[PDB]
Length: 57
Ligand SMILES: [Zn+2]
Image (tube, rainbow, N blue to C red; front, side, top):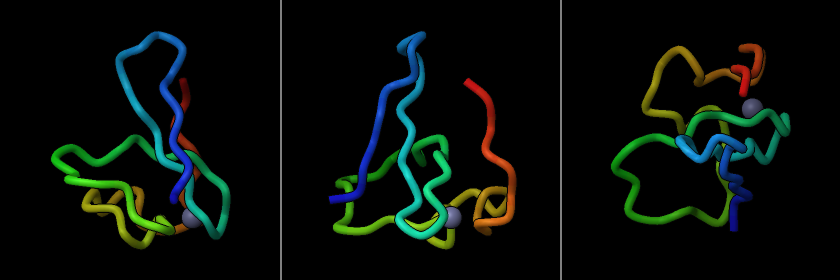
């Protein structure tokens, strides 16, 4: 199952891309974590390519 973490402040879960290992803010409204998750899965088009730098926090 795709790896997730909760940010230290507690306001945001992040999911790790199984290809590039960057952490992406978890898309809202997901019914489940998939077996593998990639930037390419992101409903947010700004964080859909592994080359996009990882957001802070
Ligand atoms: Zn990626």
